Image (cartoon, rainbow, N blue to C red):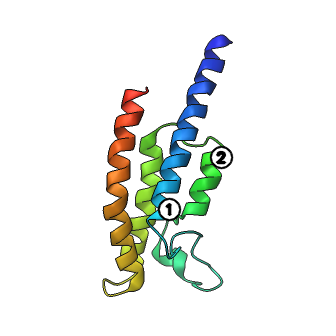
């Protein structure tokens, strides 16, 4: 149908906007602490601590499959990255500190993306 195509064009454009958002958020992680999944070879007990792991490479795979239907879903995944880190790692660690900085700096990027998604439909 012509409606299914119009919907697919909307999802495509959302994916385009989320791709830019993701690149901007990931620049706020210059040390690449959140770039890839926590290694189960190197942290064998991680899944006993964290039930829903997340990282920027896993978000990128979902993105390119047009697996995000709205910004809320995308934010959920970003929020997992931060919140998982802040639970697993203690306050006085480079890891926890990196999460806090990502959170604070990403908030700005996400504040305007919410307006761009409401604005452009």
Q: Residue 120 carries which label?
A: none
Residue bearing mark 1: 26
Residue 35 location (% of width, % of height) = 56, 69
Where the C terminus falls, by quadrant? Answer: top left
Where the N terminus falls, by quadrant? Answer: top right
Comes first in the chain, label 2 or label 1: 1
Q: Residue 64 carries which label?
A: 2
Q: Is mark 1 on a helix, strand or loop?
A: helix
Residue 60 location (% of width, % of height) = 60, 54
Question: What is the distance, in whole Å, between disc 2 and disc 1 at their CAs?
Answer: 16 Å
Residue 110 location (% of width, % of height) = 37, 49
Asked if residue 41 is positioned above or below residue 16 in the image, the reply reads below
Asked if residue 61 is positioned above or below residue 48 in the image, the reply reads above
Q: Quadrant of residue 117?
A: top left
The residue nearer to you, when weighing 21 against 70, is 21
Asked if residue 103 is positioned above or below residue 111 in the image, the reply reads below
Binning the other alpha carbons within 10 Å of mark 1 as few (below 14), some (14 to 19) or many (20 upward) gives some
> Residue at left 47%, top 37%?
70
> Residue at left 42%, top 73%?
85
Residue 120 location (% of width, % of height) = 43, 27
């Amino acid at each position: 149908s012509m409606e299914q195509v119009a919907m697919e064009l909307r999802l495509t454009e959302l994916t385009r906007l989320l791709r830019s958002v993701l690149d901007q958020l990931q620049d706020k992680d210059p040390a690449r602490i959140f770039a890839q999944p926590v290694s189960l070879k190197e942290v064998p007990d991680y899944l006993d601590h964290i039930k829903h792991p997340m990282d920027f490479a896993t978000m990128r795979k979902r993105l390119e499959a047009q697996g995000y239907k709205n910004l809320h879903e995308f934010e959920e995944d970003f929020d997992l990255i931060i919140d998982n880190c802040m639970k697993y790692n203690a306050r006085d660690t480079v890891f926890y500190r990196a999460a806090v900085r990502l959170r604070d700096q990403g908030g700005v990027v996400l504040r305007q993306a919410r307006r761009e998604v409401d604005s452009i439909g």
